[PDB]
Image: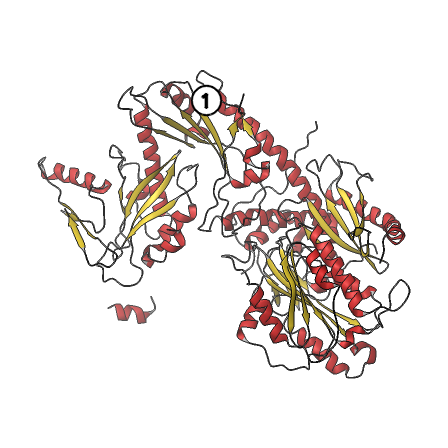
């Protein structure tokens, strides 16, 4: 029946790896804030990630968190910890100098090397011991091709207990220039989710910052209890 | 003889569907598990109406006390 | 040797029998539930390659003890029935007339071996009763206890040989209680591959004397029952007061345990109705909920383009006490670095309501209180 | 294109009264409870039977 | 006689019933049962033992 969701809906503990793009483009103070005016993409990201972690910890507590930055290659700050303080210690100390492009191969390799995926005798009824999910906040172009990944990476995505959520900050809807390339690169990220389901978000550099917070909130949902992205609506007060 | 014998050549959640269809069939087509990727409206379902099913069990405990 | 390691050595044509037996994880009432298969031998010419094993020894938990029975198959004749050896229990008299499933042995049915062993264990029970016949004192109880079929046919008994001097006998009763544990909730284990097993409560009675004096009772509970009642170590049972009348003791424990179980399960199903109604209504924006016990829920809502969270915490007395609502901001942090949040527990509520009425009243409370909470978050919280 | 939920859709869809779908999602949860027990009893490794209830120790 | 590869030296459930049924049908209450258990004495299969 077209697309099928086999996984049970149970509140398993989450291992959440949050990836931040550190580019010169992230130091742009063009995001409008609902209090005063202007704000930086990185400071909004710090407030957003701190709020996300503080909120997730108050729910069930058993959740585990990790922080990763992206430059020429992925880099691990603090991870697989149930105490959020560690993460905040590494979070409020970031530089955004961009001296190279961003490699997905390195990120997949580091994530695979730092944690293993689980398996169960029955994936349709037996709830897994934990669920692995990775959030990527990115803005720079991927340069389009970069080949079609490898067998181990496709197997990583093939796992029903592994989730990849993405937020892309782009000028495709602002400029409408090279809009073909912007939409094609978003679709390049949207052609990997087809391994089960996953959440994707798009934001303009005009903001306001609200649309980014309003975005991170939507990623709080537990991936096994979270409905399909296209079905999710929050304005339940008309 | 064994060679001649060898060459001779001698997926829905059925429990959920049957329990849903047996629980208050007054809802008619309400028994479903497929939706349009766009709008939140029901799509037709192929699980069929024909199976015996076993272990039909309590939906909610219908009791009320105080103290 | 773990079963998953043994099942790689057995002849493939025989795997299903042992698979069914292992997966049942018991035969009788077991109590200890620590079933195992130990000794495994080739039972064929040493040069037979690949999976080949067919002889084995099975540890069947019975009453309080464990019987070590050797079972024999022949790999190159899989259709044929097995053969049995009852370890050092020589006096065991298995009546071949009662073993219908052995007389009608059918390899086409994987559960056949289990049915055979089951009937054998029933005959072993009868054999232990045959041994009990010599005591008379305990038969006084046994007869009256057998007159209750829901107990008599869900019962097991065991007796130790005479002491060389004094001639005292040790004995055990085991009972499966006929209470509806079917509606007990689920819970996640460490291994997940682990199985909590059949939801049962077992009552074991042990004696020091061949008479009705000095009795040690124990009540064993399925892991799910331990989770439902908050751990075995926090629950007590009335000890036997004196005289001889288990026929008057067991009804008390059954009635009391049914009272406690219904106490918890009523609350559980009412919480499930609440969470089910709230999902039906606002699931399009659900964040998380306790799929194991329905004690917590967390929803993400939007008011005029501003996001906020609501955490619903349900107490043990959910049908009686009001569930605690907790509004939380996504933008504001307090001085302590915690997110700005406010709890409501005194609000419009009636314990008699159903899921739908409570969900609609909660939507009304949202529409009426969200602006107040937002103004308060701006007043107290910092961005 | 249609999207299929093995355990049913977890919300009241368009054109349905949620007051009557409450019981539908209750049925989803009951079916999951009863199904998980049957799927668990097929696993080889069995969980320990924990500790017994002792009578109230006096003195 | 009977050969049971890897087995305890004591006659089985089936064997006792069968021996007594043969004692009945052949009218010989002086029958004997020769039980042989061959087995291997090390993992290496360098030493074997036939106990009868």
Q: Which residue is mark 1?
A: C246
Which one is in front, A228 or A23?
A: A23
Above or below — where is A3 with respect to C334? below
Where residue C177 appears, x then y in whole percent? Answer: 49, 31
Residue in the image at 28% along x and 43% along y: C103
Residue in the image at 90% along x and 52% along y: C379
In the drawing, does residue C180 fall left or right of residue C267?
A: left
Name which quarter of the figure residue C44 lies in: bottom left
Residue in the image at 47% along x and 43% along y: D48
Q: Chain of mark 1?
A: C
Where residue C199 appears, x then y in whole percent? Answer: 51, 40
Which one is in front, C187 or C115?
A: C187
Residue extending farthest to the top is C243
Badge 1 density bin: few <14, some 14–19, many ≥20, Cα 10 Å: some
Residue extending farthest to the bottom is A178
Which one is in front, C319 or A93?
A: A93
Q: Is residue C314 visible?
A: yes
Q: Is residue D14 visible?
A: no
Quadrant occupied by the C terminus of chain C: bottom right
């Amino acid at each position: 029946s077209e697309v099928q969701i086999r996984t049970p809906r149970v509140n398993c503990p989450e291992k959440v790896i949050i990836c931040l793009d550190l580019s010169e483009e992230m130091s742009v103070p063009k995001l409008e804030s609902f209090n005063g005016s202007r704000t930086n993409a990185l400071n909004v990201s710090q407030k957003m990630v701190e709020m996300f972690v503080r909120t997730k910890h108050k729910i069930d507590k058993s959740h585990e968190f990790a922080l990763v930055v992206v430059n020429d290659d992925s880099a691990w700050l603090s991870g697989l910890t149930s105490d959020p303080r560690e993460l905040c210690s590494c979070l409020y100390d970031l530089e955004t100098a961009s001296c190279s492009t961003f490699n997905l191969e390195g990120l997949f390799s580091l994530i695979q090397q730092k944690t293993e995926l689980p398996v169960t005798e029955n994936v349709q009824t037996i709830p897994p011991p934990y669920v692995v999910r990775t959030i990527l906040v990115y803005s720079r172009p991927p340069c389009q091709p970069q080949f079609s990944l490898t067998e181990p990476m496709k197997k990583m995505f093939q796992c029903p207990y592994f989730f990849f959520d993405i937020v892309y900050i782009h000028n495709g809807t602002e400029e409408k220039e090279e809009d073909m390339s912007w939409k094609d690169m978003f679709a390049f990220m949207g052609s990997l989710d087809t391994k089960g389901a996953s959440y994707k978000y798009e934001v303009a550099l005009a903001g306001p910052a609200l649309e980014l917070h309003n975005c991170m909130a939507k990623l709080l949902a537990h991936p096994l209890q979270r409905p399909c992205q296209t079905h999710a609506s929050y304005s339940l007060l008309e | 003889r064994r060679t001649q014998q060898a060459r001779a050549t001698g997926q829905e959640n059925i429990l959920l569907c049957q329990a849903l269809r047996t629980f208050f069939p007054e809802s008619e087509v309400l028994h479903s598990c497929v939706i349009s990727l766009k709008n939140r409206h029901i799509s037709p379902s192929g699980c069929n109406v024909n199976h015996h099913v076993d272990v039909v069990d309590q939906l909610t405990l219908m009791v009320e006390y105080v103290y | 040797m773990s079963p998953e390691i043994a099942l790689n050595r057995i002849s493939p044509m025989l795997s299903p029998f042992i698979s069914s037996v292992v997966r049942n994880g018991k035969v009788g009432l077991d109590a200890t539930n620590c079933l195992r298969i130990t000794d495994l031998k080739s039972g064929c010419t040493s040069l037979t390659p690949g999976p080949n094993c067919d002889r084995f020894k099975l540890h069947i938990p019975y009453a309080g003890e464990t019987l070590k029975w050797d079972i024999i198959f022949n790999a190159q004749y899989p259709e044929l029935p097995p053969d049995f050896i009852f370890g050092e229990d020589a006096e065991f008299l298995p009546d071949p007339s009662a073993l219908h499933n052995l007389a009608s042995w059918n390899p086409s049915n994987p559960e056949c071996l289990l049915l055979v062993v089951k009937e054998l264990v029933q005959q072993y029970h009868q054999f232990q009763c045959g041994r009990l016949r010599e005591s008379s004192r305990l038969m006084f109880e046994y007869q009256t206890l057998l007159e209750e079929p829901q107990y008599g046919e869900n019962m097991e008994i065991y007796a130790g040989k005479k002491n060389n001097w004094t001639g005292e006998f040790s004995a055990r009763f085991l009972l499966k209680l006929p209470v509806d544990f079917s509606n007990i909730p689920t819970y996640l284990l460490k291994d997940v591959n682990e199985d909590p097993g059949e939801d049962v409560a077992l009552l074991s009675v042990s004696f020091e004397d061949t008479e009705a004096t000095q009795v040690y009772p124990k009540l064993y509970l399925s892991p799910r029952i331990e989770h439902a009642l908050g751990g075995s170590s926090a629950l007590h049972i009335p000890a036997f007061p004196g005289g001889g009348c288990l026929i008057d003791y067991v009804p008390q424990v059954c009635h009391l345990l049914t009272n406690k179980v219904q106490y918890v399960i009523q609350g559980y199903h009412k919480r499930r109705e609440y969470i089910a109604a709230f999902l039906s209504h606002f699931g399009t924006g659900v964040v998380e909920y306790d799929a194991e016990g329905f004690t917590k829920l967390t929803l993400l809502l939007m008011w005029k383009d501003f996001c906020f969270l609501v955490h619903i915490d349900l107490p043990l007395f959910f049908p009686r006490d009001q569930p605690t609502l907790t509004f939380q901001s996504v933008y504001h942090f307090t001085n302590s670095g915690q997110l700005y949040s406010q709890a409501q527990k005194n609000y419009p509520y009636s314990p008699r309501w159903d899921g739908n009425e409570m969900a609609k009243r909660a939507k009304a409370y949202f529409k009426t209180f969200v602006p107040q909470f937002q103004e308060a978050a701006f007043a107290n919280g910092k961005l | 294109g249609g999207r299929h939920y093995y355990w049913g859709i977890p919300f009241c869809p368009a054109g349905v009264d949620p007051n009557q779908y409450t019981n539908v999602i209750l049925c989803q949860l009951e079916v999951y409870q009863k199904s998980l027990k049957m799927a668990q009893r097929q696993l080889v490794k069995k969980r320990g039977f924990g500790e017994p209830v002792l009578p109230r120790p006096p003195f | 006689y009977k050969f049971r590869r890897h087995s305890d030296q004591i006659m089985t459930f089936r064997e006792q019933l069968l021996h007594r049924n043969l004692q009945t049908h052949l009218s010989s209450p002086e029958l004997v049962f020769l039980l042989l258990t061959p087995s291997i004495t090390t993992e290496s299969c360098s030493t074997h033992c036939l106990e009868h």
